[PDB]
Amino acid sequence: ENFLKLTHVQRQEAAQSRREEKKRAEKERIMNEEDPEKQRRLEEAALRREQKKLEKKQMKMK
Amino acid sequence: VRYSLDPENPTKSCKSRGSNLRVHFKNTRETAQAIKGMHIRKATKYLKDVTLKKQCVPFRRYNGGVGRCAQAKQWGWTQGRWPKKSAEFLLHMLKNAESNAELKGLDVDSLVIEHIQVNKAPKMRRRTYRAHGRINPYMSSPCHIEMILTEKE
RNA sequence: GCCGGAAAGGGGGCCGCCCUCUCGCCCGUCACGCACCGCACGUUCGUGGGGAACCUGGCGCUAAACCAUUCGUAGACGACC
RNA sequence: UUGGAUUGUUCACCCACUAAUAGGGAACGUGAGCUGGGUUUAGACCGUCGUGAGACAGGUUAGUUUUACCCUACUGAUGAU
RNA sequence: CCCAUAUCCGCAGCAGGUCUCCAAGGUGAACAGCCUCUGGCAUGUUGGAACAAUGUAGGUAAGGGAAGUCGGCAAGCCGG
RNA sequence: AGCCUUGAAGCCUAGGGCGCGGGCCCGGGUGGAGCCGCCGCAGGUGCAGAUCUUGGUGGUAGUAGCAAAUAUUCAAACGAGAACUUUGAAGGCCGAAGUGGAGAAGGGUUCCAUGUGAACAGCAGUUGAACAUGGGUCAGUCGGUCCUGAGAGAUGGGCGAG
RNA sequence: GGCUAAAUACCGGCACGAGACCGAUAGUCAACAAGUACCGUAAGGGAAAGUUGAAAAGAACUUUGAAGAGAGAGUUCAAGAGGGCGUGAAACCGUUAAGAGGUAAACGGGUGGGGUCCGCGCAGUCCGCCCGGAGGAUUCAACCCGGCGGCGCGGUCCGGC
Ligand SMILES: [Mg+2]
Ligand SMILES: [Mg+2]
Ligand SMILES: [Mg+2]
Ligand SMILES: [Mg+2]
Ligand SMILES: [Mg+2]
Ligand SMILES: [Mg+2]
Ligand SMILES: [Mg+2]
Ligand SMILES: [Mg+2]
Ligand SMILES: [Mg+2]
Ligand SMILES: [Mg+2]
Ligand SMILES: [Mg+2]
Ligand SMILES: [Mg+2]
Ligand SMILES: [Mg+2]
Ligand SMILES: [Mg+2]
Ligand SMILES: [Mg+2]
Ligand SMILES: [Mg+2]
Ligand SMILES: [Mg+2]
Ligand SMILES: [Mg+2]
Ligand SMILES: [Mg+2]
Ligand SMILES: [Mg+2]
Ligand SMILES: [Mg+2]
Ligand SMILES: [Mg+2]
Ligand SMILES: [Mg+2]
Ligand SMILES: [Mg+2]
Ligand SMILES: [Mg+2]
Ligand SMILES: [Mg+2]
Ligand SMILES: [Mg+2]
Ligand SMILES: [Mg+2]
Ligand SMILES: [Mg+2]
Ligand SMILES: [Mg+2]
Ligand SMILES: [Mg+2]
Ligand SMILES: [Mg+2]
Ligand SMILES: [Mg+2]
Ligand SMILES: [Mg+2]
Ligand SMILES: [Mg+2]
Ligand SMILES: [Mg+2]
Ligand SMILES: [Mg+2]
Ligand SMILES: [Mg+2]
Ligand SMILES: [Mg+2]
Ligand SMILES: [Mg+2]
């Protein structure tokens, strides 16, 4: 357990990197979506998802 | 938190937990004993088949009135059911344990669900209405859950 | 190798040979072996029954049951065809 | 070892058929099996008794018949060794 | 605002109870029953699959016609 | 010149024992601040029951059940999520003594809008008469107000311990 | 016909002090937003409910999931104290370990089998005397000095009380 605590920073950094890669791939797929109506629906859902995350964060902070 | 069984090796073992999960405790104890030793791909596949009624859940300890099905002759039992709310609660929890073994860098395709127990949570209380002006309890039986997976190659 | 055994079937008799000793049994000669110093479950059936996993080879073996589906000679559900 | 008329009847009695229309038991078998005609609450009528309230194995009429999902037994249905 | 099979009283979003106003077309004697228009609703605290028994509520039964039962109870006949 | 933050009470204990027993002493754990031995004193002083009292929890049991009043179906939208929300198209019911449109008594914010999905709405809900925010009831002519009805009720008087 | 302080009474009121009292099912019904919530048309009836920690230092931040919920991280002596949070028993339940299983279970007497720990088992007691065997003291008896104490029919010593 002590070793895992020592290694704790590395695991968080790796987890953050894998989320950055997943987010980058999601943006690339949205960019690559040929149909403008599909692209808009995906973009609106992504933005609303972010907004829900922001509201949830603000509620937890409150 | 303080679990019941501690893993034999904390690095290659992931944990999960659930408190006041509005499921049925008897159903969750049975679909947890069905999962108790499986491999995590076997489990997610089984628990999806339970929701699609391609495999069942043998009801062994709480089997009053629990009718007989044909898909229980694989467990050498006669009675069984297809708990959907209870195959989806300890599937969102098997997903949580997956996303907790990736936070530890384990091999998700090598995880065996090693320890899994279901406890009994505080009952929530409602009331029904019966004949001759009598009111009765209509209490809910929630459960606590907690699993521990482990890399076992 | 041939024989005979079925009630819940005999590792028995016999044919041979190319093997090998005159020891095996009785009565004696001849000396020896831990003679562990008075002392308990010793001495067999026992290459026991079950269970694991190991080495070492020889010959060989590559299936079904259940579920899902289907049927209706069947059926509360299972079961059954 | 029966079908019916009368009676709440048990009993009894008669008609008809029949081989014969024997007797009985099982908490006077059997009300979470039924019915509720009788008996046996509260309403009322008549008779006899009592000054009276009331009484009458004396008649009359109307009168709520609850629950099994438990264990066993039994009947079927899975399965177990 | 509700004024009632969810805003009231019955412990409740309870088949109960609770005072009135207005009042279309057809059939028909008719404010009866049945279909419809205006207006309203989504089957009355849930759905899916089966189609066993025993129930609950409706039906129909050859021949006989109360032999059933304490008793024609129930059902049936009749019906304008 | 008792024990105690170098760990008191309490509780748990396949640990060691004592006593015929009531009971007791040690060890380990948990805990975190008070406690006991003796000689006397005092008492609201020892529980298995009382159809005991209060609280908690089981088997029954994932069982009974979620069956009065004919009935739902398709596509789309919102959404993490749709048998149940919303729109549209079908099919149906109520069938002017209505499941319509308005009022009295009663309720008291149930009204309207936006949001929420914890609890509740005996399944679910993206919905609600739920929850949280805010709004909303405008009178010389509509009623009350006024008048008497059945009746209630002062003064005078009478009665009365009051 | 009339008046009249003091000694005397006081489970209401204001303000006080105390206790061989109870210690949150006790003590007032009420330690707490208690004659409150609630019930009844009314007269009336009438509860349950105290405890995180020394200090909120009340868990930033990362992560899965829509969320509740978790997994990490951090605070603290301690979250094995995490907003109904001191300690956290019993019934009841879950899981892990060990054994067992057709006369319901349980039980008393007797053993045997297995476990769990303990003995901190695994070469087994010490003690007095004496004999011998090797060593080491500043050491015994007896005398002298000083102190202390006991006893003395010091037959009947001096002086006290
Ligand atoms: Mg059982
Ligand atoms: Mg049963
Ligand atoms: Mg049943
Ligand atoms: Mg009811
Ligand atoms: Mg009632
Ligand atoms: Mg009898
Ligand atoms: Mg009987
Ligand atoms: Mg009866
Ligand atoms: Mg009668
Ligand atoms: Mg009478
Ligand atoms: Mg219907
Ligand atoms: Mg309704
Ligand atoms: Mg419906
Ligand atoms: Mg006929
Ligand atoms: Mg005919
Ligand atoms: Mg007759
Ligand atoms: Mg007859
Ligand atoms: Mg009739
Ligand atoms: Mg014990
Ligand atoms: Mg006392
Ligand atoms: Mg007791
Ligand atoms: Mg059922
Ligand atoms: Mg209306
Ligand atoms: Mg209206
Ligand atoms: Mg509204
Ligand atoms: Mg619900
Ligand atoms: Mg004007
Ligand atoms: Mg007066
Ligand atoms: Mg005087
Ligand atoms: Mg004093
Ligand atoms: Mg208290
Ligand atoms: Mg207490
Ligand atoms: Mg009290
Ligand atoms: Mg208490
Ligand atoms: Mg407490
Ligand atoms: Mg502590
Ligand atoms: Mg603590
Ligand atoms: Mg403290
Ligand atoms: Mg605690
Ligand atoms: Mg076992």
Image (spheres, coloured by chain):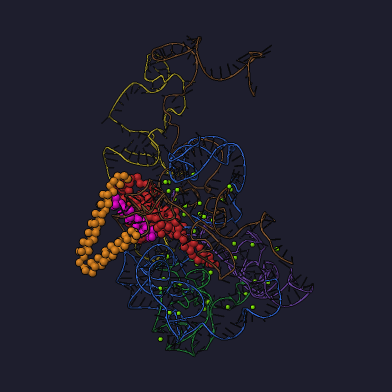
Chain colours: A orange, B red, C yellow, D purple, E green, F blue, G brown
Residue G53 position in % (x across, y down) = 42, 49
Q: Quadrant of residue B52?
A: bottom left
User: Residue at 33% across / 53% down in the picture?
Assistant: B97
Q: Nearer the viewer, residue G7 or B37?
A: G7
User: Is D71 displayed left or right of B145 in the figure?
Assistant: right
- In this image, C72 relative to B102: left or right? right
Quadrant assignment, res B56? bottom left
Q: Is residue D13 above or below residue B18?
A: below
Position of F73 with respect to D18 (left or right) is left
Based on the displayed image, in which of its 4 quarters is residue F37 positioned?
Answer: top right
- Count of residue discs: 0
- Examine the structure image and report whether residue B94 is included in the region drawn in magenta: yes
What residue sits 45% from the left and 60% below the top?
Answer: B124
Residue D72 in picture, x, y percent from top left: 53, 55
Residue F88 lies, with reference to residue B61, above or below; the image says: below
Q: Is residue B18 visible?
A: yes
Query: Which secondary structure class fits the magenta region best?
Result: helix
Q: Of residues F28 and A25, which is closer to you in this image?
A: F28
Taking depth in this image into account, of D13 and F69 the one nearest to the observer is F69
Magenta span includes B140:
no
* Residue pictured at 39% horizontal, 55% vertical: B19
Q: Is residue B12 above or below residue F105?
A: above
Give the image location of residue B32, x and y in percent: 39, 54
> Magenta residues?
B83-104
Q: Is residue B69 visible?
A: no
Name the side, left or right, on which B148 lies relative to B140.
left
Give coordinates of residue E41: x percent, y percent: 41, 76
Q: What's the residue at 26%, 66% (across, down)? A: A44
